[PDB]
Image (cartoon, coloured by chain):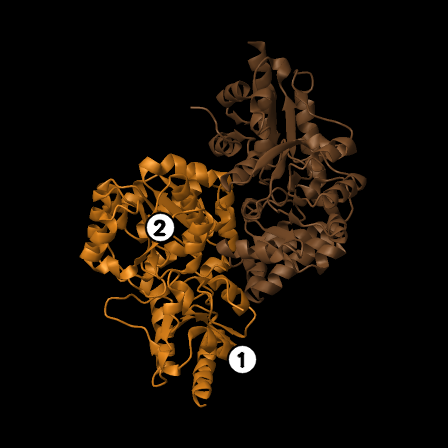
Chain colours: A brown, B orange
Amino acid sequence: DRYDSLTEVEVEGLSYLYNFADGHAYHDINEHYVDIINNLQRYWQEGKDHSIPDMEKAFKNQFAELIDSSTLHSTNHFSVCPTASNSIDIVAAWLHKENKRTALIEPAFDNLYLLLKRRGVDISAFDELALKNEHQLAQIVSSGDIDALFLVNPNNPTGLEMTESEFVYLVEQCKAHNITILLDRTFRIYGKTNFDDYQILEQSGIDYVVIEDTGKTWPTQDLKISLMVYSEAISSTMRLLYEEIFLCSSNFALALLKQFVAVTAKFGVDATIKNEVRRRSETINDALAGTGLKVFDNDEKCQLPLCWIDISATGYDDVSFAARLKEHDIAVLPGRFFYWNSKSQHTQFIRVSLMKPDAEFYEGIGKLKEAVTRILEK
Amino acid sequence: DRYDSLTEVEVEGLSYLYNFADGHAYHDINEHYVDIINNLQRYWQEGKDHSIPDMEKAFKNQFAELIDSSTLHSTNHFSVCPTASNSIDIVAAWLHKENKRTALIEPAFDNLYLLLKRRGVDISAFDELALKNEHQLAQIVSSGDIDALFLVNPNNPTGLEMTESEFVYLVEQCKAHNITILLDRTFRIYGKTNFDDYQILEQSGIDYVVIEDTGKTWPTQDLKISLMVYSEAISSTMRLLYEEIFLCSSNFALALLKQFVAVTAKFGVDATIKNEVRRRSETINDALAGTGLKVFDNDEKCQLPLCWIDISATGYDDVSFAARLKEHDIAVLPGRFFYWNSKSQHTQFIRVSLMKPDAEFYEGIGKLKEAVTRILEK
């Protein structure tokens, strides 16, 4: 009885007709990407015709071109994992080996906490809001209690996203107290920013690891690629840990996702990614309008491919409301596990994932509004 | 000056013209598998049209039919990892969590040792040849110094393989002393035996994990599937640890590798796998005849996609001989790292992997025979 993790809920949700639990990219191949699937053999062949090191660097440089980072394009200190949680787990093992006290962002997707904990890291919580408040952040980094800071930018599920100023300030302060910055950029492509985080990190001279992901952005049936990019000074040990578990990732997966990334650069994030996101976000906001559930929104957040919802006016807590919705064939994520250090004090949110197969999504949202108003009427 | 690991050598080998270092399956798609590549879209579509749980069971059951195990077909106590090292790492986490003193087979591919050590497992070494000598095995199991036994069957790089009676005896002894069995079956399809090891394990009632893999068998550019199968009693905890890292593997990879497994079942292991292995083994044996390099061979071993070579007659140790070959643009693995508890006592072997791209392989074996001749002419 009871749920121990978000992933447990997501596994259960795989059996429901309308699964809004896991936030993995599972929408349909839109018109811009169809030629890739039509030409799967071309990318099979490209992986066959190139060396593993050449394919790693080619995907990395294609990504650096898409995000326009001359610094990512020039660094050779990186590894490629098949999933971003693998990259995180390697970081956790490094954090433990180097005896680094780590403050972890809260809220966060809970397996970030679970992986750090399982590796034996000394973990403290730190408020995501401190990233947009110089005074609070300064108190945290100057305390003498921490050696590393693990962030998710933009953060899941709130969409909190740092400005250039805030990131520069963040990097300035960790440098002054010899703090390593762990940056999970899984949702980077959804950010409304456009600046060179790698350049700011490299110019600074601090120790860092940045983790990228394709899995929350390009729907490739969880055939994924995760760049793990790190500073020169910690490179030798990071690569040693990586090599304990991996020789390389798949050249076929690299060739495939390289072309997803190149197509997004050619037609822009809007035509290929963000326009459908905005339409899905509007569809859920409209469906929930006037129901009492309050979609989490603010002036400064970016639009994650996720909806974070306050249900306090329902009088229900997240697990009980998710249970009632499960009766209607609808699976959503209870939100308390995102508050991994303080679950009991954050029981009023659910999360609804938007990047699901197109028909299941739009039909599912209609079923959700009916379910919410039927549950509320009784 | 020293190498940290076999994987470091393998990564270095990726840059050499004739790379015989890592053992991953990189040979050309043969006549029976070409239709799979011609129909990549069909397997992309199959992944899109089936649920993650249904695809997991479909691959598991296709494999169970291949190996003729009704026990594997009937069990739902399994998870699906993107790589076999990920499965090993989860088992290592389990062993540390349950305080299990583990005896690990020696020799072994060394990242097994490294991953167990990184997870904090209390490791002891145990002679692979104890699996073919009942009183040697009895002493180790009744010692009261271990709670778990980590085996690779058949073993890499010796090709040692347990007979059915040797396995029955091993399980009987483990059950007597309440020892958990961890079985790395990565090289299963190369084995000469065909008995139902899952049935023997499950009916014994002992705790176990079996790890399967596609990457040393089917050439899918390191797009891989690893089945991790385990006893009912530990099934809860194993799944919990799996879910800290993974929600699932890729439905696209599952559909693809299910078809590779199916085609192997349709035409037979010999036609699709073992005949090519025999051809390549005969090539290198012929190349090295009358050189002083003595290919490791014995009556009871199976034919791995690997050639284990005693270079004693050269006067070189493994690392110096490998460095000489590197000058001739040939990369091989020094053997001492496989004897992970006793490296300095085992410096006389090199390993040459066989399942490399076809043209590179046959040309490279010609160049290897030329390099050995020329090196020995001094």
- Of badges 2 and 1, nearer the viewer stands 1
- Give the residue type at disc 1: Glu
Q: Does residue B378 sit above or below B183 in this rendering?
A: below
Quadrant of the image containing the N terminus of chain A: top left
Tag on residue B327?
1
Left-right relation of B98 to B118: left
Quadrant of the image containing the C terminus of chain A: top right
Q: In the displayed image of the protein, which residue is found farthest to the right?
A: A165
* Disc 2 to disc 1: CB gap under 8 Å: no
Q: In the displayed image of the protein, which residue is found farthest to the bottom?
A: B377
Q: Does residue B344 sit above or below B256 in this rendering?
A: below
Left-right relation of A49 to B145: right
Left-right relation of B145 to A243: left
Query: Which sits earlier in the primary sequence, circle 2 or circle 1?
Result: 2
Tell me residue B354's x, y (percent).
41, 70
Q: Badge 2 is on which residue?
A: B63
Same chain check for tags 2 and 1: yes
**Could you say whether the residue bearing mark 1 is in a helix, strand or loop?**
helix
- Give the residue type at disc 2: Phe
Which of the chains bears the disc numbered 1?
A: B
